[PDB]
Length: 57
Length: 57
Image (cartoon, each protein chain N blue to C red):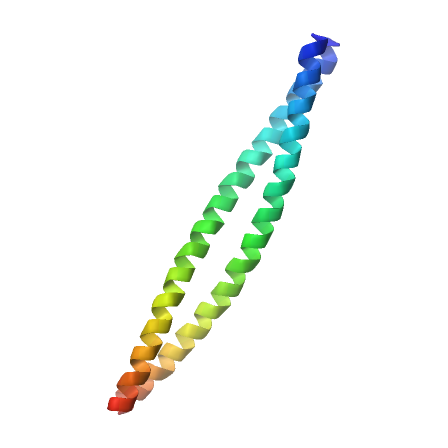
């Protein structure tokens, strides 16, 4: 029982480390996604203006 | 020692569950990033095409 308990606690520590790393990755990717969403909105505005000018011409 | 083993097991289980959830979240957000990047590339190409159309018309 003692050996099994030691192994289980080591497993738990490893899982906690993995969870911390995953949190870091998630936050980084979230920031990148927000930046690209803003970029796409700028793209949309540019397209709107170009379409209007095309219609006028 | 048996009670200690039970506590270690439950802590490991909780940590693994959180790890799985974080994995799913990172997968989803990374897929979103990939899709948005493809859209942005297509949008740059479309913008160049629209400017060419403006000039010719």
